[PDB]
Image 1 (cartoon, rainbow over the protein chains, first blue to last red):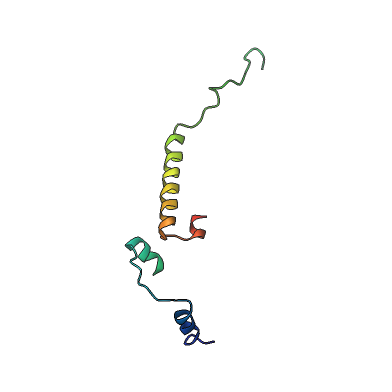
Image 2: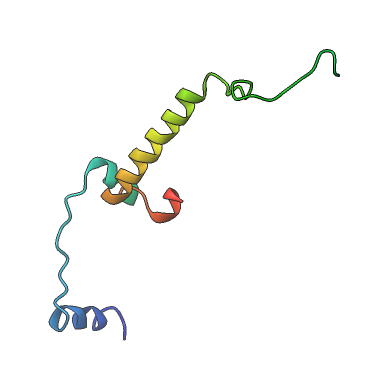
Length: 32
Length: 48
């Protein structure tokens, strides 16, 4: 479904959680 | 072509002098990039 229940599915069932990543400045530049 | 004569030995295959540095430097950038590729700095296509 849309990204309000499909996102809900990942949390309640598959244990998803947006844990923060500590990116190095060399890896920070790659994503941005 | 006889009186002068020509032949092929092992030291007549004269590699250019600067190959010692260029290949060494080429290996360094391949070592660094393949080391950062495991850090997530670059993706697979960039390494390829």
